Image (cartoon, rainbow over the protein chains, first blue to last red):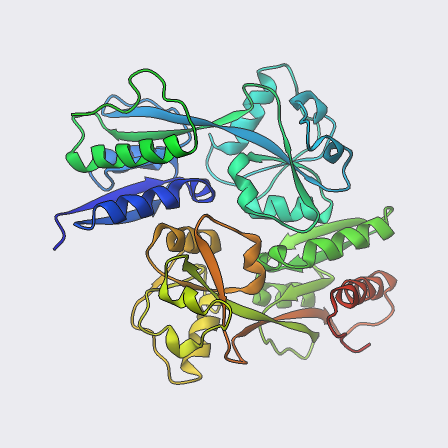
Length: 222
Length: 214
């Protein structure tokens, strides 16, 4: 007996973070629900929500539309993926700053419509009057990491990319406080169903385990 | 000059980067150009002189192309930590154990591809999984498994990806494998490509893998 099908849009990179354990726990606690997962970019999620193709969208862009509302879940730290022989890797335990990377061969990704993670990264550089001269855009994250592991350059990546460990690939912390990539949950701009509120609580629960501290009024009830 | 090397994406989780890095370090003066592409695309590209060597996973046959089996990589089953099949992690399981499970095939790109490869191995033994879904790529398959719907057959080097509560189980059927080939046109005097062969031979020896002929 399925009480309801809940449909969830998500950006692909979130699979390397908490998304799967959140969905697994949500399913487990709510065996009366059928949950369907649809990979789609943040802009695509907006249209999908409006016409009911999905019920919640987990995205990385803050893109306003009156018919949608969103809540920032957390800011994920960025890191520098480097070859283990790279000078920057001597700072693995201490971290580095964006201005240390301006003369390095940087692999941006993905190849997809902009804005995306690539523009996101370049905007953080531009916010501090930094203009990396050696830039190359590649198809997606694992191509970027493979090329770093091969000796082709370095890449800025979400911290949860560390789910991928390749031989002679290292991840160096980036210390600039604004060196982050957000995670949002977006829903239609109306009162959330009992089912979506249940999803909020699952996120709350996992976040508490991760020791994340809740901001004021974070994920409403009722 | 420079050397153009075609490769299938799944090889990035294996020894490809390590080979390329050792190769680069030995020849800092040479520039290397790595191009992601399928095995059929590599073949046509070799014949047209658009790449120098192609690392692929398909048993192709062309008069123009000299192909060499480097090694067979084992297949594994990606499962949730809680899955019954994960009780045989140390022993391993067989293809026939999987036919009533929800299997995630990938990628969704044009066939023949890894999906066709996996389904062909099942059908080579009269096995026909009824619950199949073809998804876009490997990380989607793994994420969906970890979220608690499905299992997926994957190359063993896929273990580079470790997701929370994702576990990989060995497959025991001897033909549960995916080959790796190096392909070049029927060619001779080229020192850079001979040095690529030797770089592979060096990495394989260090790993303990047996070597191909020369």
